[PDB]
Image (cartoon, rainbow, N blue to C red):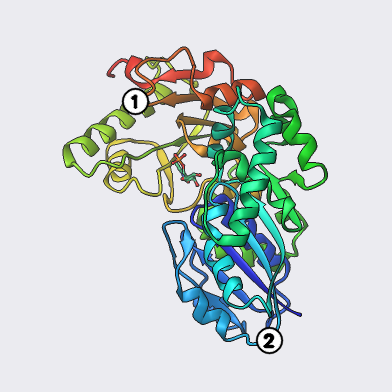
Amino acid sequence: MKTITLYLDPASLPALNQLMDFTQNNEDKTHPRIFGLSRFKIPDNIITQYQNIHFVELKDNRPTEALFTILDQYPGNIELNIHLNIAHSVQLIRPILAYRFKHLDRVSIQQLNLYDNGSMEYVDLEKEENKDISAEIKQAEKQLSHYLLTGKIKFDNPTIARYVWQSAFPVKYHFLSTDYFEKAEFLQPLKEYLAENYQKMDWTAYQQLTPEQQAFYLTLVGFNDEVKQSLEVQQAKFIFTGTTTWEGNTDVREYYAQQQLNLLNHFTQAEGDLFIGDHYKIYFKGHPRGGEINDYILNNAKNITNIPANISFEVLMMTGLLPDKVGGVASSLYFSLPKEKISHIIFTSNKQVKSKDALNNPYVKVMRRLGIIDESQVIFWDSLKQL
Ligand SMILES: Nc1ccn([C@@H]2O[C@H](COP(=O)(O)O)[C@@H](O)[C@H]2O)c(=O)n1
């Protein structure tokens, strides 16, 4: 059968790993490929070098029907090599299964490779701490069978359903935290169930690439030479990480901008509660969707070096360019960082958190369970004095 590789991800981390897989296989210029990476654009100077390369929009975390137009161009027997975001795997594969239904004679699923979205998978797993995980797996497997037979989605445990694909297809899972699955006691049944179908995320794959493939990869992920040089000075580095807000209200976005500037000052100013000392070069890493929030920092701070905000932070993990220290507002990007590199992580007030909620939320709990952070490194945003 002819193999078609599908790279699907609405987010960042899976895409980063999928673009590594493409780079590792980039000598094959005609292997059929379909890219559905909402946050990444393959430069046309690379697209033109490949044949049978296709692109599909994602909408509501699934490929659009435009996928069918692509697959119709391959009228023989086809086996699908599918790369997915774990958290969104059920929706991402939905149009693929629908197409297979219409072409059961010639379309088969060869294998799945699944990659963590980031913190969201582990948080979601925390909320299942009190469940009979062994029973949830069996039910999820049963309901995955119904999905595969009817095309209709109904999971009593949508979270555990993300981890039962091996009951249907050859699968390999790539986890940001293998420790979590091995340390969390309530997850022991799941760890044993997954058996030899998971592995730790290949963060050091970039180091095994060829010199030219390394440059290939950096072009795919938007990390140009100028930014690289900046993060290679022989100086103690601290990177301040920013955040964003859904709200459109100018007013509110302005408050988030003013408050993130204040948080920066708590790290970098001597009177600050989070002062890291005088011996660090300071970088700012805005949130990709920060918009004016990011401009507020650069326009009103000083002695800071900007790292373009649309770069996914996790690139620095995939490339070995992490700083000595990272600090800022809680983000998925922290789940993937070494413990000794964390200064302080700050939390924003919302529905569940109106105080340093005794750290009774899953995010901190996961991090503490894994030992990435201690209580002294958790900060509630509103408790910080206005400097
Ligand atoms: N300062 C930041 C904040 C977020 N991000 C990107 O945004 C993604 C979503 O992060 P949040 O958990 O903060 O929404 C992160 O996984 C990372 O790829 C970033 O690259 N720099």
**Residue at which label 2 appears:** 76
**Which residue is nearer to you in this view: 227 or 220?**
220
Q: Is mark 1 within 8 Å of ligand 1?
A: no
Q: Secondary structure at mark 1?
A: loop
Which residue is rendered at x = 62% and y = 61% of the image? Answer: 149
- Please, what secondary structure does the residue beneath circle 2 have? loop
Label 1 crowd (10 A; few <14 / some 14-19 / many >=20):
few
Asked if 281 appears above or below 205 in the picture, the reply is above
Viewer-side label of 1, 2: 2
Q: Give how far apart the Cα atoms at labels 1 and 2 are.
A: 52 Å
Horizontal and vertical percent for residue 226?
Answer: 51, 57
Considering depth in this image, is 363 or 265 the residue closer to the camera? 363
* Amino acid type of the residue tagged 2 in the rendering: Gly
Q: Is residue 66 left or right of residue 368?
A: left
Quarter of the figure that contains the C terminus: top left
Q: Which residue is mark 1?
A: 351
| Amino acid residing under circle 1 | Lys
Which quadrant holds the N terminus? bottom right
Q: Is residue 116 left or right of residue 201?
A: left
Q: Write down the quadrant of residue 74 in the picture.
A: bottom right
Residue 314 x/y as whole percent: 57, 46
